[PDB]
Amino acid sequence: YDRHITIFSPEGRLYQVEYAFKATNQTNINSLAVRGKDCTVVISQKKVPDKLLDPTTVSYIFCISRTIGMVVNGPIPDARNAALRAKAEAAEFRYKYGYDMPCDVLAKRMANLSQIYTQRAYMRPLGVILTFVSVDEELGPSIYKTDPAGYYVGYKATATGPKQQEITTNLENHFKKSHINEESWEKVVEFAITHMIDALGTEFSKNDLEVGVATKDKFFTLSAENIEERLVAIAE
Amino acid sequence: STFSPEGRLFSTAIGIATKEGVVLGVEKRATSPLLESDSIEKIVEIDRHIGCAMDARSMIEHARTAAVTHNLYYDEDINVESLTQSVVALLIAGHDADDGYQLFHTFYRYNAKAIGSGSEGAQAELLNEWHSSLTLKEAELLVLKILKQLSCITKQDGFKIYKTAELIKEL
Amino acid sequence: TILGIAGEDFAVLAGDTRNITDYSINSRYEPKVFDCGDNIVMSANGFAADGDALVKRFKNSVKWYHFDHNDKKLSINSAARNIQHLLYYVHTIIAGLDEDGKGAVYSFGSYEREQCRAGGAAASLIMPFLDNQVNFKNQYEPGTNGKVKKPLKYLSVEEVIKLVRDSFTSATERHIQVGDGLEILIVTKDGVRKEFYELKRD
Amino acid sequence: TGYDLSNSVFSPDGRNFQVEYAVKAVENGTTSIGIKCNDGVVFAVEKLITSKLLVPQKNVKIQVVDRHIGCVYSGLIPDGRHLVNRGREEAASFKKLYKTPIPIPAFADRLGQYVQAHTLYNSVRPFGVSTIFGGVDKNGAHLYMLEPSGSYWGYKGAATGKGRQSAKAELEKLVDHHLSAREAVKQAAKIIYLAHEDFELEISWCSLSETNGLHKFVKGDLLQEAIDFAQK
Amino acid sequence: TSIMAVTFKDGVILGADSRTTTGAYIANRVTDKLTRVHDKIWCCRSQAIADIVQYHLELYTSQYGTPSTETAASVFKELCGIIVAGYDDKNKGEVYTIPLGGSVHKLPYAIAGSGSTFIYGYCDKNFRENMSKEETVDFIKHSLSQAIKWDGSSGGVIRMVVLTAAGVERLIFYPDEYEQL
Amino acid sequence: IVTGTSVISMKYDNGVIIAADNLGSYGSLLRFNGVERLIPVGDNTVVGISGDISDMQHIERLLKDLVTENAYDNPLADAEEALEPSYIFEYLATVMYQRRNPLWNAIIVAGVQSNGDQFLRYVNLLGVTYSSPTLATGFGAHMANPLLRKVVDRESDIPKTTVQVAEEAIVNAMRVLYYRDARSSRNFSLAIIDKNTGLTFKKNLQVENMKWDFAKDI
Amino acid sequence: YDGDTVTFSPTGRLFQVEYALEAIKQGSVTVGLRSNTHAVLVALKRNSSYQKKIIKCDEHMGLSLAGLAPDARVLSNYLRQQCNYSSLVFNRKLAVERAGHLLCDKAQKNTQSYGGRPYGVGLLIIGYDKSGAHLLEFQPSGNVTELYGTAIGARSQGAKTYLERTLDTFIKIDGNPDELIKAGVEAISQSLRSLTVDNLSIAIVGKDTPFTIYDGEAVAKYI
Amino acid sequence: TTTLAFRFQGGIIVAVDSRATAGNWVASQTVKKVIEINPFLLGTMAFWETWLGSQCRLHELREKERISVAAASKILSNLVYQYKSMGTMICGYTRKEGPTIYYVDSDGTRLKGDIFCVGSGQTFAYGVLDSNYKWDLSVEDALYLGKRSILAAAHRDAYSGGSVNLYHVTEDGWIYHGNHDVGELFWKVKEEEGSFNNVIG
Amino acid sequence: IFQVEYALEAVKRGTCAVGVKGKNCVVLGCERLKLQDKVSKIDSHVVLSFSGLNADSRILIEKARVEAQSHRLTLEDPVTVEYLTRYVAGVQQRYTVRPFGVSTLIAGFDPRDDEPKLYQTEPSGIYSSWSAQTIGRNSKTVREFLEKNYDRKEPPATVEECVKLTVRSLLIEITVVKPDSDIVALSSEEINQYVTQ
């Protein structure tokens, strides 16, 4: 029964947590986040299989707070649960401690919740990987990623999804050759889209992407027209 | 707390219900001469006009509490059918001014009923022997007959437990 | 003000229909005595809201009684005991026929069955006159030198109606809170009869 | 096998099987659809006649929440009623706190969080219904559809139930060839009859112009016009 | 205190004095009494519950989207006088007042605090619908200056917050400026 | 501390008339002049409220919740299963008695029952309720009832009281209340609920024909 | 998959609820029918005395049970409590449709929460209110259906088919309480494989008729 | 109110008045101030006793023997002390206690004794009991003593009177020796004894 | 129930205890390594003996003592032996994650009474009265001895007869309970004189 609840197998492995990682890939979309000089950009594939869907609602990027944004890899119900909990925690921190929750504090709090699910047998882990992006008041642009095991760490740039390894190789190549040195968020968004295209070998329309930009005192999501401007700027 | 696919959930006490009273009897069946027969209370009172013949003690405590509560609340003797739905195989017998003398064993009112390992033959004997014109004397004697093959509730006496030697001699 | 009188195979429960606050009349016809069925008549005066709550809860209790006993006519003593256990800044009076067919008036826990009982503001104006006229208190047979008391005969429902009307007319005369109309409910073997009599409206 | 006997368990594939079985329960339900018109939403459901003894209309299936949200679902109808009761409680609480009718996206999120919560614990069962719901609020018309997993999205048109596939095939044609509310009612009737291939058509709708944004049922002459158009 | 919210042609202007007193002693003569509970929603007590209301409004903004000024007043009411003034492009500038009774009243302009008593007649005669920004500012200056001149527990500098579709603009007027009005 | 005073009403041969002034007084200060205190709850019911305005708004919220919840799973909520004046009155009385943290109000629920009987009942913060051919609340219970009771002294006067007679009586009672009540306003709302015509709700009525000329002699 | 109420089968069925439905088919048939003015319950009891199938909730409503009687007593207790609450808080006679929906919402809880079991009793509820005469059929799954007539319990299919073919007739029976009872007793007879004065039970409610039950000699004239 | 209970060779005599007043208004002159808890227990008061009788019925059903007077008085005193101006005697007979009187009051005290008088007229009842009481009184003498002791309090105490209800607690249960109207009783006593000389008539 | 029957097995492995009640007293006797070096008073008038899991007997005895004192605190009268037996049986019933593997003999006298009482309780929560009884290991063997040496029409008349019968049955500690709160364990030398005799 060690594979049905979060208890150790003879190998010391928590098989339910390992299966929870597998669930994260079942939405089959890839995302990447890069840090600019003064901003953070998140790119995510907005795959819309059904023509009757309203694409405006299909979205895995969440505005957790004025400054923090979150992109989720995994089932949308669990993703929305995580987003609601993160919004609640950010508001409670702003209330208790008088200032906006830092990105990494939110990541730690969410990873501690995830760890709790990983040790109490009553509760299953959420099958979502949470990637928080913000421009911290102190540390500047930040990317923190949390996983079902309760592990989290900060990133220079990160990718997540079935083709995570390829996007990671692309980013590693660029970082070796070269944060992304840019003067405004549009250029870093264009760079992120370019590397997404190259890693995935697939061109994107304004409908295939969802983009979130973290800037000083605002995390905002690009509308389809804004993403169209970026795609034109790349086509040029 | 589960249903079977066929839809259903997964001593010998003999009673007669006459129009002059309801008679109950039990085989004490002491396991040894050391067990004090005085303490084999297999027929018990539930109320001044209600008794039953046998989890037992707890259910009887709750039934007695319900009956006294009803009497306190309404100053009326609880209806036997109401008691059955407000409270081991049971023979519950009592009297009231609504349905008179009743005997119950989910519940079903019975003119006469028996329970236990001898129930299968006892019910046939009752079916052959019982008649509406039974006076309390013949009812008591037929109780003893079926046992060999006491207590009563009356409008004057209420519930009382049994002179029993005199009835075996009269038997 | 309410008034219950038990008699020979009848009982009456009467009360004035006026409703007041401070020195102002709220309504001139607010019925105060209720025919509760089962040949029981009841009235819960005192603080209005608690009386209403008590009546409502007693109606709930009697509905449950009817449920458990297959719509059996609730006896006056059973109703009285129920009303105790339910008990509110209220002075309840219930009247009806007992199991022997005699008139019965119950006053309220601590219920007391009594031959007559008044309640409300003008109970003090009404009750002594009823003691004198129904119970013949302080009356002796003439010429006996105070040795032989006047026998306690029973009054017919007509005489009791007259007594109630005159008692409430006097209370209306001398009590400012009493009297716009008189509501009298007679309980007998036939059922519950309702009578209304006008009183002075000042 | 073995990993699908409980609600909290992930399979080695990463899938929660009890939710997929709840989806299987939905696909057995009768066909219900929703259509978003330029200023409102239209709901329709095929009400299968079990016998001639059913009263011809009074077994209503579409449900209103507050006054501006309408809900229709397929699958275990009692679970749909349970979900709608929770939705009514949520809307009532929101109106109590904030004096304003709950926005449709907010209501959708509340219902999704409730349905998803039933997939967290082994002690509770997933909902056996996919619920099309929508209405009109300060931001216009919204149409949503829950799945037993708690997943939901906004839709231009939605269909679920046994005939969901045919209904979807005709919703695609609606969207590709355009739809005002008046026309939307008739199109909903046509789509329900096409998907049916005895039953009762029940239609409802909520349009800013034609109902002032409040949810109303289609009755009388408009209902019959939809009937004869669809038969036409 | 002497707080004053006035809707005008382009939005709402919320203004207050800067004096706080404990008895006759002025505890603080430069207090900022205008409280930003949400981006375009500002309130004015006539502190802990202000934090609670900001908490609940951030929670609302995260769950259900941008709250209205009526939403803010509702949150005050359900937690509970207050003048809640705000702006949005759907409703434009709004003023709500929540006197001690706890009832909520949407108004064209609102005055509160001890100083408001002395300028009920003045504001009634001088207020006009859809004034310009300059006219609204002058109106508030004169009203609050009279309230300060009469109310002992009111004084110091006059602060204003101008809420408009353009943005939030803060103004300050010193006694050397308004006492001569 | 914000309160409204006057609610008066009488029943007549075909329905009920109810009126109230549009004022909210902050103690001695006539602070708010637009408060509406008559709350229609359908074509057959109006709930006039007096006392604390915050509790008045609370009660309005509860009434709208009633009208919302009654329509759930109720296809006849429009005509046959619609809320009666009596159902609303009993709900409100239950609310007041539950809170009684009492709601500091007095409420007159006026309307016509589905069978055509005029409904007119009172309830206050103590849960005290009564019915009468004429009802008034607060300061009107002393000045308005004597005037209205001259029109309908008893039950038998109701069928002899026409629409216009009751209307003019109510208007005159508002004029007298404005004369002699310090916490009253010149502006009032009036609602007629006729069994034939249904709810006929008038707003922003004016107290007119006041007499002041005799002041010059004093 | 069938060992508990919170598990779906791989095909989406709830085996425990289907077993609870099978529980009803064990009990004796009860029949319900109505015109516009009157609604009638005709129940076949079984013995020893016969168990009473009819239960009275109000002067305006009552019900009969098929299956586990204890589940019936619980559901009818809850129903009476809800009617009492409605009269307590509104002086409003609880509508039959609303009472049916309350039962539906109570029964559904047991089919979704672990620890309990579905109610193994099916109920026929008849009542009269402002909307007229009503007849509801309640099932363990929580489903409630408003019907012109129905029969539940063992071998009820014969009575149900008879009611189907007789529907055109007994709908027209307005102002004739006895003819409805006659049609109902004729219907329940089709479910036998016989009726007696002591075995049969009848209940009726309508415009002028409060809910009343006939047993013993009272049903002799209808047999 | 005036209630007295005293023990003598023949059991217990319990005598009470009947008056009840709301201030100066005499609400009733026929109130029953003795509750018959059991055929062997009398509760004298000057809900509680309904609770005690319910507990006694439960004890009778559960246990083999009747509830003791000590147990009943302790139940009542515990209940009163939980809700801590009232005074009661629990008078009864038990085969293994004999005749027993327990005094219980609103303060929570519980006293076993031979003689107790309670209520506004208690001092006047004591004046007669203390001077005329003997252990070896005959049953008739003890009944007369209780009647006379309540008569004294009824005469001198304004809030005491109406009628005297006599109870006798014997080995076979309590005996109700009837109701005596103080109006008739005062005069009868005055002629037969020659007492109350100051009273005209 | 299965767990209750396994608790009965645990009881049957426990050391045997025996009780006999005579005309005037109840006598309780009990069957007590090289380097190692039963009857519990519940109140001054009632004693409780047990056989089975010793650890569980302490929970039972503590609960019984607390109830015996709480009865005197709530009601003046000390507990009856019957009442205490009923309470102990209730506790045993209620804990049927696992039952007590304990059966008890409860003996003593009623308050201000002189008829000796002897009762038994078993893990299921059943209880009954006995004139002589035994529990524990080989309880059947010695109960069969009592069933023929104890006479219902001539029970033991004095302390000597009760102790003699108890010692014969056991063949040792002996507790004699007598009215008016007289509980005493016999001396080792006295028990030796009985055994030799």
Image (cartoon, rainbow, N blue to C red):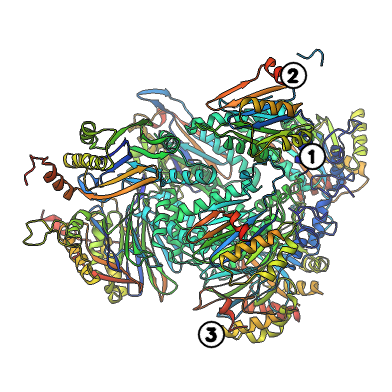
Amino acid carrying label 1: it is Pro
Label 3 element class: loop
- Name the spot of residue C63 as percent of width and height, x first: 48, 62
Residue A136 in view: no
Q: Chain of mark 1?
A: A
Residue type beneath disc 3: Gly
Observer able to see residue F109 = yes
Q: Helix or strand or loop: what does disc 1 sit on?
A: loop
Mark 2 or mark 3, whichever is nearer to me = 2
Which mark is on residue F36? none
Residue C143: image location, x then y, percent: 6, 61
Give the labeled residue for mark 1: A125
Quarter of the image holding residue I32? top right
Is label 2 in contact with label 3 (beta carbons under 8 Å)?
no
Label of residue G175 in the image: 3
Badge nearest the viewer, 2 or 1: 2
Q: CA distance from mark 3 to mark 1?
A: 65 Å
Looking at the image, which residue is at 58% across and 43% down? E166
Name the mark on residue I196.
2
In this rendering, is residue F134 above or below H181?
A: below
CA distance for labels 2 and 3: 100 Å
